[PDB]
Image (tube, rainbow, N blue to C red; front, side, top):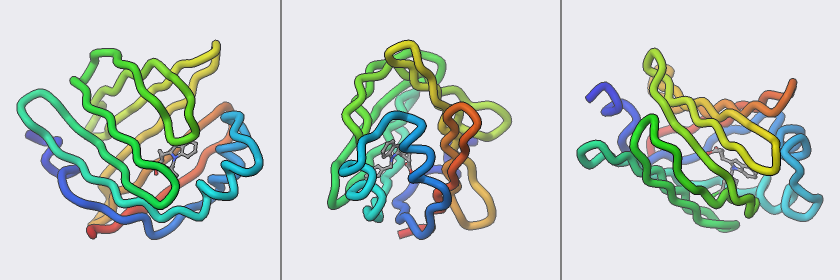
Length: 133
Ligand SMILES: O=C(O)[C@H]1C[C@@H]1c1cc2ccccc2n1Cc1cccc(Cl)c1
């Protein structure tokens, strides 16, 4: 139960370069503005082999439940319909999303008391930092 360190309730405190990430992904103007304002709460839980990541915000709510290494269907906050696979590599959750011939990778890691979310599309990276709620 190493995934233990992720479990909890988390609140966004900072975001860097996320507009550029969203642009690279294909998000349109109005969604970038509204999504970029949001300060979501993320709730991570584990029950047996199933991990659940729920995000609640003023903009959209999202929820994914998955088993590591097992592809699943996901609806993203920006309404992409993707095929997702999440693995644990050296204590980092690595989440690859595939859609329309494109790919993006989201890494989630624990650093000090924070949960750091790094979103990468092509050469663009963004960092989102969460603290315990
Ligand atoms: O967990 C994170 O920090 C980022 C992985 C999540 C992510 C990807 C993505 C792509 C496009 C637009 C927004 C997007 N959001 C953030 C986000 C913003 C507003 C409300 C909600 Cl529920 C989620």
